[PDB]
Amino acid sequence: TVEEEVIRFAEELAEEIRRVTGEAYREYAEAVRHLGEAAKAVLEGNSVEADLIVTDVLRLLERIGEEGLVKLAREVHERSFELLRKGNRVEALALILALALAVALTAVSKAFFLLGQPARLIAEYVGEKLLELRRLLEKLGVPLPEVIALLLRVLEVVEESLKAMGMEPREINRVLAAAYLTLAAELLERLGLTALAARIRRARELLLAGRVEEALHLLQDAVELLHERIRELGFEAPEELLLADLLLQRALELISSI
Amino acid sequence: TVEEEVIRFAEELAEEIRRVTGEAYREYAEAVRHLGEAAKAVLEGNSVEADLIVTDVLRLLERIGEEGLVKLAREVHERSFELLRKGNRVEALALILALALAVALTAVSKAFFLLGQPARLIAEYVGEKLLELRRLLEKLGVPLPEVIALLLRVLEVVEESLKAMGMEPREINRVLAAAYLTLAAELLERLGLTALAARIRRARELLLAGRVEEALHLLQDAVELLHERIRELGFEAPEELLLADLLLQRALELISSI
Amino acid sequence: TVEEEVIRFAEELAEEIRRVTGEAYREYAEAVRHLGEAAKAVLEGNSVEADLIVTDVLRLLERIGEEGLVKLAREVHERSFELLRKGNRVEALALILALALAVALTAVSKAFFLLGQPARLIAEYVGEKLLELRRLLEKLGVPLPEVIALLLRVLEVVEESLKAMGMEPREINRVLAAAYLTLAAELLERLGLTALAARIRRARELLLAGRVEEALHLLQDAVELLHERIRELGFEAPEELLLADLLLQRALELISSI
Amino acid sequence: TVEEEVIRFAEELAEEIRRVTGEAYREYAEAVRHLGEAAKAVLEGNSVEADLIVTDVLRLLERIGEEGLVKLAREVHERSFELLRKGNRVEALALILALALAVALTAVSKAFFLLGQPARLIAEYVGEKLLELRRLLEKLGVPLPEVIALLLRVLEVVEESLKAMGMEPREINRVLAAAYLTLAAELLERLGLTALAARIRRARELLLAGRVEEALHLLQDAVELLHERIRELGFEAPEELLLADLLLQRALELISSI
Ligand SMILES: [Zn+2]
Ligand SMILES: [Zn+2]
Ligand SMILES: [Zn+2]
Ligand SMILES: [Zn+2]
Ligand SMILES: [Zn+2]
Ligand SMILES: [Zn+2]
Ligand SMILES: [Zn+2]
Ligand SMILES: [Zn+2]
């Protein structure tokens, strides 16, 4: 039904915030439910109530005090207003869902860092949530490059929040690299390159266990073989290969900077 | 089977710690599983393996650094050794389960306070866990006064941990009063005095909402009615009435000191 | 028709603000009319426009600069959103009306204190407005304990505003005690205890005239006789007696602290 | 029989510490014999005696004062407890054997450095002991990647001990590179690439004789040829080649840092 998937995504995201944290972070759950209501409103035709709800969420996040989240909220407000005036329902829905996921991941990461959890669980949870959002957006109809751009925007927001809170840079780089690696592994696996995806997952697992250099070399070998495949295909290479290559290069940079 | 209830209690307690916190507090889950293994060893006949496991748990708790919980662990060690040598299996099992519950509640309260949770959720969770332990101990066969003494021992451990962590006294008093109120309400309801139990629950709910004086007066009126019933019954008053009266007096003093 | 009563209540409240003050306090009248529009919107089925209007009122009160009023507005926003999502129309209406009455009483009390009016007329006006709100809520269907909790929240907001403005504590205690006394007198009279209600009104009148100790003793005698009646009834005492007893105890505390 | 190999390994390891050192390092032999007793207990079915013995070994190593060894002991304790509860006998046995080898190698390396021995004999002894452990684990049934991870854990413990004791970094890098080189040479030889293994051994021998740059270039040429073979095979490359490549890269980094 696709729409029911969006409403269930919003409700399940709010319930996941409640399960992970409880009532210590309730403004985030309120904002996520508001964004779900806005996404529901978009799907029937009402385009002004969506703008009003997005402005309400912007006020809530401004009261919360997360600079990157507020910036993303302003950008979503402007782009969603313009697209809804023009008639691009799908991209406005994608922006609303990306904002909701960004708020949820910010709350979850803040709770995990305050508790004192290691970077492994944060990395797996962020990767799983990004995978769920990617599947939802692909079911909706958003083109893949825009989906990847939205996911990178969400990851940028999460990284900014973690850096501002006080986390040491190495752990932030580790979790961002793990998220990029799982995204790239999913992208490669979708195209049928199961062994390459398995190698990427092995590299991610070795990275999360403290074995940095071994994961670095595994990733470099995977990158070289991906380049061989891409340049053998020619100019008919599906966008999955190029997006996975870019994500792997970002992961290489982040892992090297560790 | 009663025993299966004991091992399931230990495993479910560990799983609840994992659900509430995750992997940020893993030594507590290790200690709870060790105490569950000790309780399983006691029920089979082996009395020295239980002592060795309790000593291992004591070492783990000494490494953790929770002074009151270590004190409780030492007392459990001594009493369990003496009772198992004599042959009091049930009381040793009760002490082991009380220690496990104390560790679990200490971990949960520490996580909740670190997050920034309100006192309401802590109060309800502590009350529910104490109720589960009380039902298990009553099913085992421990006499009621000893069960209650163990419950206030666990509550004293939790209070000491909360004071040492840095919580303001008023919230600690509020959660202690809520725990005593729910314990007394269950004790009264077991005897059939459902209206008095309902009044006690109303007093607890008004206390948790910040309405201190109204809850104080409701508790005082309930105390006078309980005294009237107790002095009408005479010397044939079941132990439930006396234990509930003592718990209500402690809750009254705690609420007054708020 | 009940609904027409709500709309007329909002309009009459705004007109009463205008009559008492004029155009010196116009933001309060604007907020009251906005809340009346929200209450009208709730009653047809639209639950998002109500949230948007409540957020608008929150912004208006944040610009006004009344800390307690803003806190009550935030709490009303959250609870009304949750209840309207679940489907509790009546409690959302009650919260909106309580917020409107709180704004109106804050404006009226500020005007009366700025003019230099004595506490007697302030107390009578506050009591009359609380009585009107109580009758409206009882006609709507809100359970009595929740109505009393809402009225106490409104009184807390008014007390906080008066304390922050600069009023001497004795007059604030006097007006709060008078409001509690008239509420308790109405509650007792509804149950048929006309003579007890008359004694409570006599105590309130002696309190407002400066005769503090005589009113204190009259109230203590009324409290003792109410306790006699309550403990003679047993556990079948209607909620009116218990709520009146709690209100009388709060009045006793406030009068003693004078 | 496989098990008899385990007890003989423990006893022969303890006898080897006695032969190399004598009675100057007796706590290490005590710990190794305790770990052998734990390994014997695991293979018989008793899973709590193993935990008690591992805790005893942890106390012994805490008294000794080797921080890395204590850390490895704690990790082995936790992982072995969890796996034995689940039912993974083989991995718990592997962890116990890895801890025993780590203690033995730490004692031997400390004695060798205190005497003033050159790095060559230390490197050969460490390589031989790691080879024996690898053969034992492969006979048991542990998968190769986990065996290699355990071997680098042991090597990390030894390296940390050497750094903390006072050895100059260059000799530590030399011995670690030699150990990695012999491990990779054995891994390559197992697959039939005997000439590549011979070249790796030649590089190790040139490294141990002070000829650093020649060994560096020989290793680089071997790495390029191994990469050629790996990329010629494709995705059907046995895990031996990938693990050898990772080990060779770590050895290359260590040699370059010399
Ligand atoms: Zn707008
Ligand atoms: Zn390679
Ligand atoms: Zn003992
Ligand atoms: Zn009373
Ligand atoms: Zn809202
Ligand atoms: Zn009198
Ligand atoms: Zn243990
Ligand atoms: Zn060459």
Image: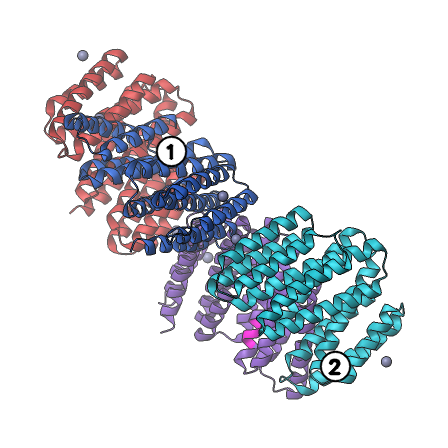
Chain colours: A blue, B purple, C cyan, D red
* Residue C98 location (% of width, % of height): 64, 63
Magenta span contains residue B185: yes
Query: Tag on residue D53?
Result: none
Residue C135 located within the stretch drawn in magenta: no
Q: Amino acid at mark 1?
A: Tyr
What secondary structure is the magenta-colored segment mainly?
helix
Above or below: residue A141 compared with residue A255: below
Q: Position of residue B213 (x, y in %)?
A: 70, 67
The mark closer to the camera, 1 or 2, is 2
The answer for how far apart the CA atoms under marks 1 and 2 are is 85 Å
In this picture, residue A232 sits left or right of residue D9: left
Which subunit holds the residue at mark 1? D
User: Which chain's residue wears label 2?
Assistant: C
* Nearest the eye: B245 or D30: B245
Residue D205, compared with residue A149, is above or below; it is: above
* Residue at x-position 58% and y-position 80%: B195
Residue bearing mark 1: D25
Number of other residues with Cα within 10 Å of mark 2, as a class: few under 14, some 14 to 19, many 20 or more: many
Q: Are marks 1 and 2 on the same chain?
A: no
User: What's drawn in magenta, residue-wise?
Assistant: B183-187
* Residue A84 quadrant: top left
Q: Is residue A250 above or below residue B118?
A: above
Give the number of the disc on residue C226.
Answer: 2
Task: Report the front residue among A103 and D199.
Answer: A103
Can residue D14 be seen in the rendering of this structure? Answer: no
Callout 1: SS:
loop
Q: Position of residue B168 (x, y in %)?
A: 64, 52
Looking at the rendered structure, the secondary structure element under dot 2 is helix
